[PDB]
Length: 414
Image (cartoon, rainbow, N blue to C red):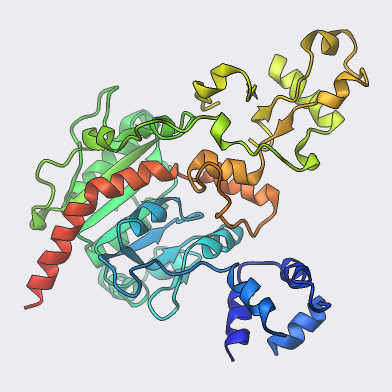
């Protein structure tokens, strides 16, 4: 009966074609989609191999340090940091079906203690005018469990004041559930958006909810709420981070995101360290694509052997945009672009896994991160993601505060 249980979980994540290929790769039996479906309605090493395609629970399972939810979860960028400090994810909302597949491939999700939602309005009922605020709150609580830390990456939309936006849905959820803390991620320029109206309305809304936001009054060009991944990984990637503390709990104390610098690694990961020395040929640019990309570059090239690539930080400006040199001669390209000899040295694109390392989902040298989707979807996913070690650092700063909050409610239960 357990074999049918694994297959249903596997089919949420992987294409039938991939599972069939994986089963054939074990080299014991011949498999097809139809035969796989038959088995879903046969064992030994095949079972063992399929196990390696699913994430294991953390080492401390089933005992967790605190509870959190994951809104606009993507592929789990914000989740990783908090799972790392013993957190239990008890609810995830993510609209993008392919992102959900990558999420499920890398995060253990027990349906007895966790729920997925696709469309958040289905829970908040924000599109239903006739539902009262209290009835909506009661409805939200049916779907979203009690939690200590709310995590959200919401989209930047212009603006009872927040109505007609996804920010409103997040606010409805914070009000219905009153987590001890929240962490919201947003675009670096949030402060400038709509002549400052968006940031002002967001901060005022959060304050009126009863939350103290870290560094709320520190809004100059050195704003500590703006954190760049460049401190952890070799690319410029800034997001604004809004950390809130429920005021009645008095947890904030001296907390400040200025302390983030304590979390910076001793030595930063280099661009060179993230690259696989051997890559499939399909990553080499096609002759036509190189014609496109070359003219663009004239109207980001990495030289992994040039000493500078130990130092350099890729701008904000991967498996398309970021290119790895394979010995193209500039002068020859200028004289005769189609030179058959120089054409053996077209640059290559980053692979999805190298993009995973660039974003912090994958350690240098390692291949633990599961990518169950197409290269195209994977690039999109990594492009849309938070920088993992930024939020791991934030979680580390919050850990003592989170432990205090859990202690408070456990004592509040007596």
